[PDB]
Image (cartoon, coloured by chain):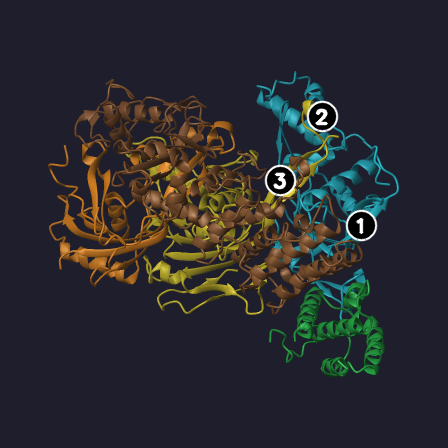
Chain colours: A orange, B green, C yellow, D cyan, E brown
Amino acid sequence: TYGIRLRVWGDYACFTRPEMKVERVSYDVMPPSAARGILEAIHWKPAIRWIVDRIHVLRPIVFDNVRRNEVSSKIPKPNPATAMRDRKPLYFLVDDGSNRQQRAATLLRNVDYVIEAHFELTDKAGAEDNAGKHLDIFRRRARAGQSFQQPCLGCREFPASFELLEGDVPLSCYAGEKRDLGYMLLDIDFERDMTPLFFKAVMEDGVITPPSRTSPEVRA
Amino acid sequence: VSLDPARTDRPYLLGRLFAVLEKAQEDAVPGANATIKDRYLASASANPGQVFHMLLKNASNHTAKLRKDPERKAIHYEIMMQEIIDNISDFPVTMSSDEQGLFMIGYYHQRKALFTK
Amino acid sequence: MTAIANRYEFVLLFDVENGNPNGDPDAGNMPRIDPETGHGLVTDVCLKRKIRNHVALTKEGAERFNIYIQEKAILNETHERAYTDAKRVTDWMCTNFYDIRTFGAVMTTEVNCGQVRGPVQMAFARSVEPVVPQEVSITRMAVTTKAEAEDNRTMGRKHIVPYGLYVAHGFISAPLAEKTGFSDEDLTLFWDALVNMFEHDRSAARGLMSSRKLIVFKHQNRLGNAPAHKLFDLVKVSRAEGSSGPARSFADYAVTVGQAPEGVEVKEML
Amino acid sequence: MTAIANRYEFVLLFDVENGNPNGDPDAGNMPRIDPETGHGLVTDVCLKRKIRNHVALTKEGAERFNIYIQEKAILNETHERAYTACDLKPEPKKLPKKVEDAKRVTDWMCTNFYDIRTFGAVMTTEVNCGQVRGPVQMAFARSVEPVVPQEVSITRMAVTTKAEAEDNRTMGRKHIVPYGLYVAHGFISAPLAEKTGFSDEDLTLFWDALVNMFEHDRSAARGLMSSRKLIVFKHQNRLGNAPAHKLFDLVKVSRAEGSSGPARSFADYAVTVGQAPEGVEVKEML
Amino acid sequence: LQALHGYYQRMSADPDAGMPPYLCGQCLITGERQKPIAQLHPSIKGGRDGVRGAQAVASIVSFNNTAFESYGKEQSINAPVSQEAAFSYVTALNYLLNPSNRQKVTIADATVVFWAERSSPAEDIFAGMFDPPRMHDLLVAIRSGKRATDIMPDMDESVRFHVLGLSPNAARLSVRFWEVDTVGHMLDKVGRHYRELEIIPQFNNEQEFPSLSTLLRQTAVLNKTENISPVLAGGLRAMLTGGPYPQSLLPAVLGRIRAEHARPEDKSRYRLEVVTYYRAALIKAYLIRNRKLEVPVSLDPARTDRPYLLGRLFAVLEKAQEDAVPGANATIKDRYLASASANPGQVFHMLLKNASNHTAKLRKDPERKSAIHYEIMMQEIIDNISDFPVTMSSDEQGLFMIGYYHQRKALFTKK
């Protein structure tokens, strides 16, 4: 009863592997990190932490290739004062030689997930901040289709349609299958200088249950 | 029958008429080196109203030749011509590409029928 | 700070005639087509580039409407700056570069990772129905090297989409705007660019591309009032009853919008 | 040479009568068609070539009015001209290391050759002269009704090599469109014109060329080709007052009320030009 | 990949056919905590002696540019793998890339390397199984649906198999596809693929199992290995995953058929065909898999699909042409095939009139009655069609092409 069951689906998705960021390669399934991101796109406040209990993979895994022209560099910081001490044009020209970068992608197609999640109050939570309140607000937003931002399947190019599941979860294509997906991105511990942390993604019956991202025994 | 005798369609009817005319000529003067399908198909499909009249004169002569002999097939060809032209109100000045395709398929449909027992 | 007050959704319909709307660098520059459905495909960043270029031309370096991410088709004749703990620099970047304000950016360094989001978001534009590009063989008069002059003519190839209508979805999130000062003036200029994107983008390759329709679902709440995926469902772009065979002009398509839920409006800019 | 200041769109109508307006290198030499609907096509490249020919014939190589793509030119030898006239040694495979000299060579290429000034060019090959986008663009011409290309077989009563076939004559064939009305759009860009140097003199010459395009293109395979309309939509400012498509649509091409059967002359078509938006003026007088 | 890592751990055990040579974080390869992360990964072999097309110094992980750097981390801390693992995977990849070992094949632009999780004869078979040259008997068996054990008892099909495809991006190389299926399962999938592709040969020198490179080459812009669309090379993942082929395949082969013409530069007696054996095979595969249609291996005159009948009709008209004007340098297949298949209503009238003229010429000449036979075939094919459609779909065009290929082959020396 206490918990959430959010469904998300979309044509495209790209959950890029950390060891293949330069030439994008997607995780076969949405990592908990992505899940968390999606959840925070609907409702979130500093007072609350989202936890992903299970991730259901409903539609089968399918891959596709897309290649895009890209920029090689982050824009440099100007200094506001010296930026105007002598009026100057500021720009970033994608046609100026080294600027141009080509970057392939190995991205999923026709994804469909059911995210089971729940809330947890952060240590900086307000004294009056009820967890039930935030549960209700998120459920309202999910039912009404409201959101802070359109949730995306990893990347902004890939918007995610979503609905709230009040009923029992539908069955997956992998309902009677077992599959070890290897070590994959759990989360990012921003407290511990932003290293990745990984888990053994053993899919079974089409449902993945990762360990708690807040577990002391996972964290250093 | 794949041939659709109930298809009152102008290019289709003209194609059937062409087929029956060719059969009539083939019966009147068998085995010649060239048939009207080989001689007049170009003009026939190009400006039908300008040549179908003379094609009909020739077919009338062929059917007259047939009529003299006991092998009066001639009555079947003449009644076929009567039935086909009955449904046509006027010959077209020109036919488009699709109308010419319909003409060809109608001709080939009617030709198949006449050869069948 | 001022900001737009409502979440917006928009469905942009544009079409191409005998042109290469967006080439595929991984397929010999042939126009992209989706492998899973056969639909033609246009990347969002291809469209964002057009919006950037159009605004750069139109606002010609006005105080609050300069553009960061240029391409070498620009002029340096005139410029000006707004000139209003690292929040100061970020909001200075936002307040005078239209593209950084609208689409977001990333800066080289911060204690943080240096991310700016911007409210606008838009997805891959895909054809309403599958497209089948045609290879066009062309020949040149002269030869480029002296070696190949050893009578003299070279044969090239051009890839064209005979026709195809592309549906481009997009989302404007007001809460993101509130962190970036994306105001109603910016939003109206943005609708202007989306309508006028392809006007200045003429070149040998693209042929004729035009924005035919731009439906805008204007919500009442700061957040939305209905799910975006359900809003997009109302724009039933389907073929006119009188047309059969390949589509070769926008008249071959009939597009209508149903009654959106009472909490969200609709406007047909085009 | 001061640049133009107005955004212009134009619509070109041209005829073909028993001619091959543009041959397809793939279908033997058959006139280009849209295979899925039968409408005839003329590559914008062909019309650009005819414009170039017009320029060369009417100016005959006067200064500021040479053309860059010619029937026997070598591009690198032409780029070395720019490098010499700029006094630079032609950097091997590369631009000059000084950006200002690069700009000067590119501008000399633009300011001299008419068609580089007009249509742009990609000169980054061996001796590198940079890139130009071209203030002027035009799309593929497409017929208003599907064309029916017919195949005409012909014979020659003489043979090139040692042959004994002539026992029948040497056969060859021509492909021709019996008739077809082609609607070719075009575009002129002020912003890029400024960056290139496209002046009103040039523009005048341009409309001239368009009107007189085909008049000097006569050949045994071209038939009788003519320009029927040049509906020009002048915008009153740098950036237009009306979307392009919204102006093209004012130009309506239909078949005359009394015309039936396949079209065989311009008179079978009724051309109507609507009222342009208040920010535009129409000079259909061309 | 950790698959690579496991392969190194496998081969490194033996003293031959391998090699035993040797801040902190979580190693994503192994999953071991607090291990020495590599700051700069060892290089991969590029060039013709490694991954073709890439520069000699190739790499999987490469953060040389500021764009790709993330969460404040630098050159390889973004991709954290222990030193040992880094070495391992690289080495295994390199050993698989050495052509002296049979575990390698080059497809289009990508180089494919495969292995079994433990020693199995599959690793010696798959080298040729998607580049066919006992092996032929095995191929016929698996195309028949027979289990591999019946031809190779030592084939333990429960062994897991891996296939990897690497494409070059200058110094960077990219993963195009990846399969980890079992030997038996993917062997059956390849069997099904070859079963779908099966078509009667056009000339008896063409091979029974068309090499995938030959199939791809035939869709190339100029019938050379370069100009193969890399996306189509990657799409034909569909061969051994068992899924639908990429939807861009049929329009690609149809585009080749449009833009092709019979080059007599082969210098054989025959002028090169437009619908070659391989293009028809690809069209058959696309129609069987994506469209779920039924397509025979040879002509089936007991059929009633208008697209198929029109393809057969086009074939007989082409035969009549090539008999009426022998040795000509061009034929309707060079020009009107593209528009006949896509828009029958506009062109079949002229083709039929031209065929009428051809039969006219043939009747007076010798062959005085094949002049009759072709007209009988036109009768019996046209008899089943009610109208010429205004336009035809892409898959209808595919059926047109298959019918044309069938009726052409069954008519080379019928008369």
In the foreground, C203 or A173: A173
Q: Quadrant of the N terminus of chain E?
A: top left
Toward the viewer: B71 or D69?
Answer: B71
Q: Residue D238 at x, y = what percent?
A: 63, 46
Q: Which numbered mark, 1 or 2, is in the foreground of this view? A: 1
Residue labelled with disc 2:
C149
In the displayed structure, E168 sits above or below E348; it is: above
Q: Chain of mark 1?
A: D
| Residue B60 sits in quarter | bottom right
Task: Please provide percent x and percent y for residue A85.
Answer: 44, 28
Residue annotated with mark 1: D153
Q: Quick one: label 2 or label 3, which is nearer the N terminus?
A: 2
Determine whether, in the image, residue E116 is placed left or right of residue D206: left
Kind of residue indicated by mark 1: Ser
Image mark 3: chain: C
**Subunit ID for the residue under disc 2:** C
On whether disc 1 and disc 2 are found on a single subunit, the reply is no
Provide the secondary structure element on which disc 3 rests: strand
Residue count near mark 3 (Cα–Cα under 10 Å), binned few <14, some 14–19, many ≥20: few
Q: Three-letter amino acid code at disc 3?
A: Arg
What percent of the width, then of the height, locates residue A189? 20, 36
Proximity of marks 1 and 3: CB atoms separated by less than 8 Å: no
Q: Is residue B37 left or right of residue A98?
A: right
Q: Residues within 10 Å of mark 2 (few under 14, many from 20)?
A: some
Q: Is residue D9 visible?
A: no
Whether E387 is drawn above or below D132: the answer is: below
Mark 1 vs mark 2, CA separation in Å: 33 Å
Q: Nearer the viewer, mark 1 or mark 3?
A: 1
Is residue D26 shown to the viewer in this render? yes
Q: What's the CA distance linking mark 1 and mark 3? A: 29 Å
